[PDB]
Amino acid sequence: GAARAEVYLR
Amino acid sequence: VKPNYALKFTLAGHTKAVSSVKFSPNGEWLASSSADKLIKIWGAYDGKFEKTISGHKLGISDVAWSSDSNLLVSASDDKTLKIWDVSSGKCLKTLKGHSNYVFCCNFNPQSNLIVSGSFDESVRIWDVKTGKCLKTLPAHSDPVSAVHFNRDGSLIVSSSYDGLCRIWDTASGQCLKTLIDDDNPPVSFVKFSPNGKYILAATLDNTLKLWDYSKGKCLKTYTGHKNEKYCIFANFSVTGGKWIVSGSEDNLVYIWNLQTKEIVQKLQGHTDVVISTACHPTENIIASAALENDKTIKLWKSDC
Image 1 (cartoon, rainbow over the protein chains, first blue to last red):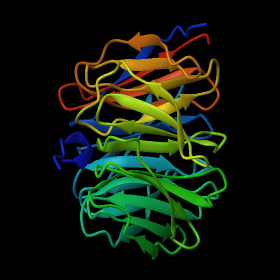
Image 2: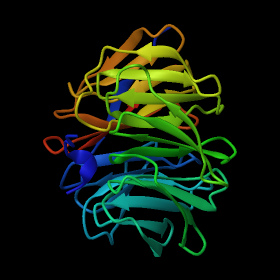
Image 3: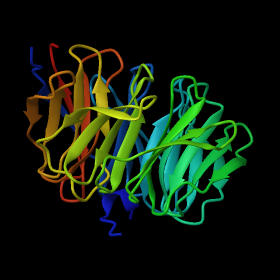
């Protein structure tokens, strides 16, 4: 996929 | 005064979430990137599909045009950036050096350098001609969400999920300024204003902020939209009235009056998060793009 289209949690 | 953006065209073709849309500086084209590993080129005024540019091994999070509209640079989960000759579709260089997903990218105004940001927490500066990595900045402590050069290319602004905005000297790589506002929400996007005097920053607490970076002061706040999860682009619209434009997690495009900070228009139509918006350089045209459940790009036109 593409990282921008995913949620990133600290 | 308020704008009157109205839906003109819907652009279908990408097979996964669209990640970024950008108009060419000459106003002729729209480039789009997607999690489907492709870049697509479309006519800016009619929305007519032009061609697909392929080569990345994994999805692409960003794409950007060179100043003369001749090249594109893309940032991918394959940990590379690729420089493309738009007219031929050729991949001129593959930029290898990041150790994790590349998230954001841009050329400098002279279009001889590329700046990139990554999940590896660094900002890299690359030579366009040779494709070589010139400098690696240990910029942040979490993924870098955005990178942008100022008006003459002397500075780079970067943002990160670590909650900081940093300004870097392009020549030396020195950290000249760290900007933060008394709370530490992830900074999801940043860019310099067209005049280079300000920085527009988005944070994952549903807020956009206009900073005077020389003074390190927040001058304007724009609220009302939903942005708590994704790195949504924001823009300065300058062709007609002076607006701030952004996508939102409630599936709308939001438009604010830059000076008053009031919401002036909300654009309804997308069926998923509006991740990216772009403003046409000469006409009052907005392009918007949405995530996985939508997969489309929309072109909106206004009289002001």
